[PDB]
Image (tube, rainbow, N blue to C red; front, side):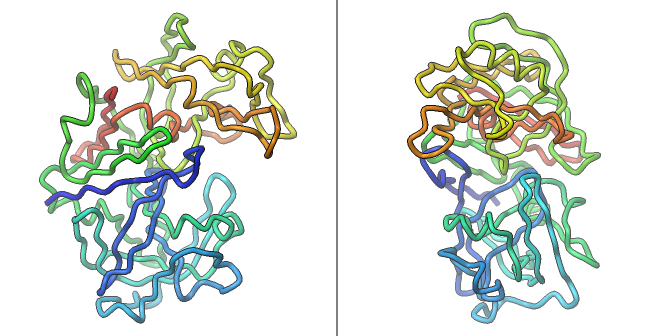
Length: 330
């Protein structure tokens, strides 16, 4: 089997992407944030504290003839941005782009933190990291991909995120029309539960390529590119007036600037992030100070190849017995 679904930016800045997901019988369609940096499929629901729901579409398990309470199971997750959610668990039928899993754990939120409530466009998350990170207790549950894998034509999914435009998540096949050149594959460590890999270096604009190993995670659920302070300083030094602002929470730059590109290495291959992808707009409405899309990972504890990086590539998440990651230009 295969599946193919369009993913759409939630706003004009590509702060996140939503993908429609069918849950239950009859189908209830929710727009979920596909997150290769976590491993829980959780939804706003009829069980979510009413004051914490503000415009989201909810899953109502009592209206699904295929929903079954997973007795005794609870979940609770905290994300790198400080947000969190928790609740109980159902199993139900879940379909993405024509690909159907029966008996998928659907984690129903009883509580969500303010950031989730305040974002009316995201109805929940669909985790695509390794199932070892799944938070369901006392019996850990499998991700959608893990449950689908054996049925797929090939044990892969691909992320093709758009810049200020829709893109595609495919399951079970590689669309050879969706990228240019060849796909370069690189080793993955699953030791931390992430799609963790090592970039071979970077360049800033038309500058020379610096060969240096940068370990980090391919994370569709993180907006920006978080890299070591040395790398980030080298980037922003090429932008007149750019500075790190402790009050704002990162590098800012004059909105009048033309940003240079940023290149990262995948083996001997190179992915170029155009400068415009690195512009996240005014820090506050009407400001002429703009927020940068490349930020320091210092104090996160891990480098994160988030959407800013991934949207410059066609990315293969290869879930073979030994997983690997593939990157192509597009």
